[PDB]
Image (cartoon, rainbow over all chains, first blue to last red):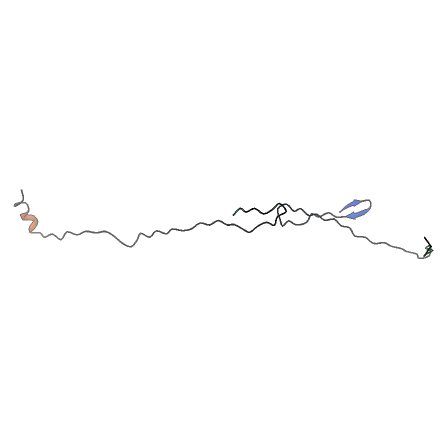
Length: 48
Length: 50
């Protein structure tokens, strides 16, 4: 897997069934962390 | 078989051309012939034949 802007993504060209049917794929694997729920503030539901 | 389908095709069925045997038997029969000639008649046949 390469490193497109700090996010690790993996190519893996898939299998072949017909004669002209290449059909690639691509994908990644995320997770987000929010330690120390002290510094966080929200002002939910503004008129907008 | 070489059929025509598409170019977004579906890879058609198998072909497997075949060979066959012939087997031509020989070892049964024969063509023969016999004589059955005596021993006295071959001695007088050097006399009464010109």
